[PDB]
Length: 247
Ligand SMILES: [Ca+2]
Ligand SMILES: [Ca+2]
Image (cartoon, helix red, strand yellow):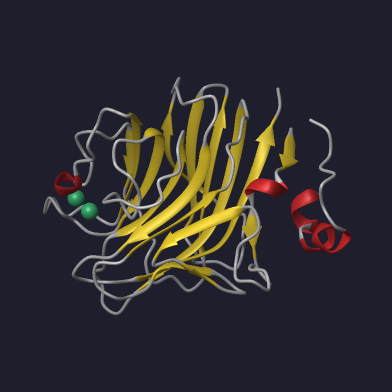
């Protein structure tokens, strides 16, 4: 509650459609155009690995083999209820690609590791956009919600199927328009909605998965990461927009 004050008039203008229940969290957000500052950094966010930010997007992991990249908020958020809207592209030659992209709310920053570019044994929630079918069950690309409390090693080989709280099968690769994921944590419920990028309409969201009465840490960083394997897609994020929800 209470409108954001630590912002310039150009940035106010820049984020106009976002400011105009829902309170825009400027300090936990990024977008183009001019996504990046004259010194190459994304204001309020740190990047690591192979991630390279530019004016229009952050290429988290480019289409080389065995790449890892991530981007994380510099500080933790402390929101009872929240909603992130993440806009991205996963592009590659051919109908099959690897490995995928992850959106995180975790207690620490997962700068580097083996889990879509970020740290294993995390404390909080990952939403995994897993493009490659490691278990051969012919059910990728898939979106899987994986909670963790610092104890679990992510089961890469089964596509996290044995550890997933919820999941849906959606092809988010090679789409005419950017793909969008909206992730909502509200009154103990985690919801994933996907805009699959067939349409110019940015609000054409379809239900994907839900976890009722989920627990997550009271404070955490938001993050996004990706990785490639033998096959390699470009994984690009165009914007990450955070909102704090009340009542
Ligand atoms: Ca996989
Ligand atoms: Ca699979």
